[PDB]
Image 1: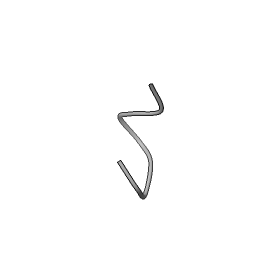
Image 2 (image 1 turned 30 degrees about the horizontal axis):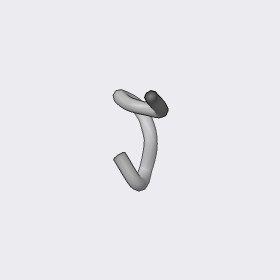
Image 3 (image 1 turned 120 degrees about the horizontal axis):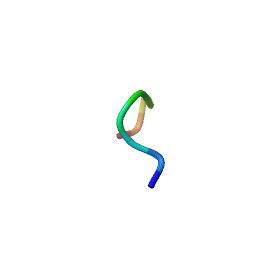
Image 4 (image 1 turned 90 degrees about the horizontal axis):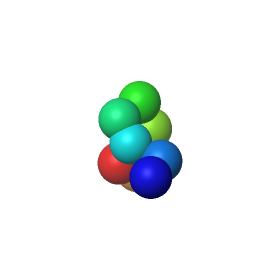
Length: 9
């Protein structure tokens, strides 16, 4: 759920 906005996303 860490997306969007994430580097590993």
